[PDB]
Image (cartoon, rainbow, N blue to C red; front, top):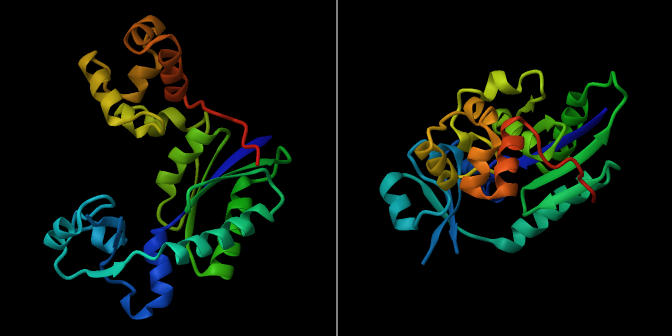
Length: 232
């Protein structure tokens, strides 16, 4: 059996800063750089509606008691390379995206539980770097990344054909990875508001609205499919 695991570091920039400044643990921390915007908001800060991308002044308005730290890219680079090297050295095909994400493939004995590979990944990363990460598990990239959302924070989650529709069916199309807000507004205008509805929509409805290939890709995503090749 061929599996795909997606690894995502928890509140990466903030976590790296907390190494350098332990006193701040458990408190609203906001990292800001490049007019300056939020580059990473700690989970505590997010409870106040603060999110990556927003201007710092607007962030201060929402979380007056937060501690603002200057962005330090070179430390984030270093911290990421360490983690990525650690992932690569496990021997599986690996594909790195940005600083905090990676997809890795694992061809496993039909009986082996993939969750064990995920528990070792979490342990290695935590033991060697102090950082927590979450791991999504499936048989393609997109579904694995969606699985990661349910694993947050500091967790592991498995999404396959068995539980896919039960977990996703009633959610809006934008819960799918690869389907954004603009596409889901266009879909709402055509009377399509859940993943289950999109999954059984007639191909022609989608292809005339989004073109021949995009129409079909939306069906594949909604059925839980996606890219299967990781390739290092």
